[PDB]
Image 1 (tube, rainbow, N blue to C red):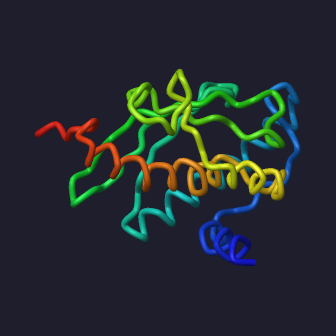
Image 2: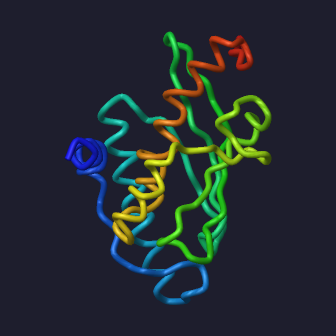
Length: 165
């Protein structure tokens, strides 16, 4: 109920995805990628209108390797971090693991290798919604909440510094 309303408040304006396809599923994967691209670009457009344009992503040709940048604002200073992930073979039933490589070894809320460690509620929330959630939802419900806890903590602990530029 509280969880259900909280999820709906975050993702209700993100286009829902349909196709059960992962990287190996040929024409159905090309279809899933159209859903993923339309959903991501709407999320970016909604983010711009809300003064929260907080990431860019691109993929390889096959849509199996994703990478770009996220930006996180603390006390009006903007912090940039490079991000990347592989699409799992069992996508979209299995959720991708976002990596923020520059933060490898700098927070306990991160696996060896730079993969962020989400709280236990994300995974069953993803599983409950298969195959409706995609990469836009991964960003909105996964990395977004992770940054909103960890970046403030790391700036305060002085492990992250803002480069004067």
